[PDB]
Amino acid sequence: DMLPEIAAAVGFLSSLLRTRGCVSEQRLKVFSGALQEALTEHYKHHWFPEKPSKGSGYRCIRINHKMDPIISRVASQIGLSQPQLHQLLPSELTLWVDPYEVSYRIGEDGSICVLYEEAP
Image (cartoon, rainbow, N blue to C red; front, top):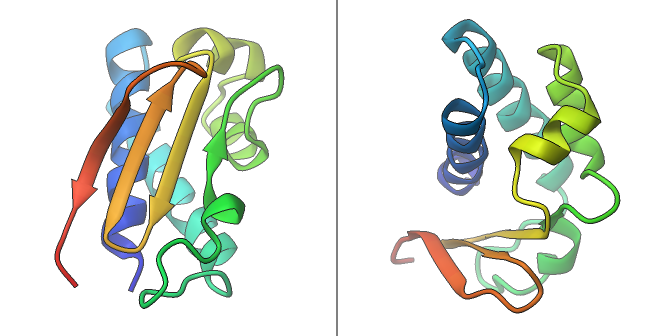
């Protein structure tokens, strides 16, 4: 039903902001909630538990020269600018949020790390 995978993904980003930033828990709670909501809306029509790769490119969260637009706008709601995000988050991040598995990679050549796995 998407909640756990989205929650794990948002929990990861929130943890990066807590550790690297000086961001209050009030703000981190707003950020976590709003991002969970935003991604739930974004992923609604692009979530196929029986085919986890289907929609994987659409759902993937990327940070390059550009910040991911959903992260940017939710971050703005808690008073973080994109320049700040560029500094607080890893610079070459890919975060895949798929049915039964959330994983990520930092840098084009970095390891693939599994954040969340669960059995269908």
